Amino acid sequence: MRGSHHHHHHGSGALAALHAEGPLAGLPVTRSDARVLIFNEWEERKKSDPWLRLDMSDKAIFRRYPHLR
């Protein structure tokens, strides 16, 4: 097994916010926090293992995080 995609967009991704209490504890406060958490995770994963694809449609956010609506 061999292959390297070396994706050049490194971003920052640190600005996203989370809920701190109740059933929502650990989850995004906003649509943009959810989008940027998926971006930050993809970018770190991409640095460890370059093959991964970034997907964060509004439907991907509501499927991962059903409280965003």
Image: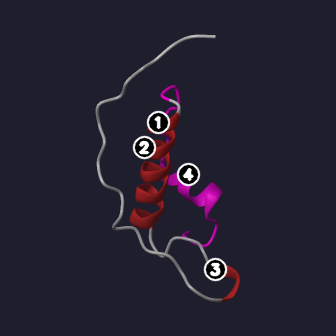
Q: Nearer the viewer, mark 2 or mark 3?
A: 2
- Magenta includes 64? yes
Q: Is residue 22 left or right of residue 3?
A: right
Q: Which residue is mark 2?
A: 43
Does label 1 or label 4 sit earlier along the sequence? Answer: 1
Q: Amino acid at mark 4?
A: Lys
Query: What is the three-letter code of the residue carrying label 2?
Result: Glu
Q: How far across and how far down the image is residue 19, in percent?
A: 54, 81
Quarter of the picture containing the N terminus is top right
Q: Which residue is mark 1?
A: 46
Secondary structure type for disc 3: helix
Per the model, the C-alpha gap separating discs 2 and 1 is 5 Å
- Residue 42 percent coordinates (x, y): 48, 43
Depth check: give the residue in front, 57 or 23.
Answer: 23
Q: Are marks 4 and 2 in contact (CB under 8 Å)?
A: no
Give the SS element for disc 4: helix
The quadrant of the image that shows the C terminus is bottom right
Q: Between marks 2 and 3, how big is the CA–CA gap? A: 24 Å
Secondary structure of the magenta portion, mostly?
Answer: loop
Query: Which sits in the foreground, 16 or 58?
Result: 16
Q: Earlier in the sequence, mark 1 or mark 3?
A: 3
Image depth: mark 4 or mark 2 in front: 2
First to last magenta residue range: 50-69
- Up-down relation of residue 54 to residue 3 (above or below): below
Location of mark 3 (residue): 24
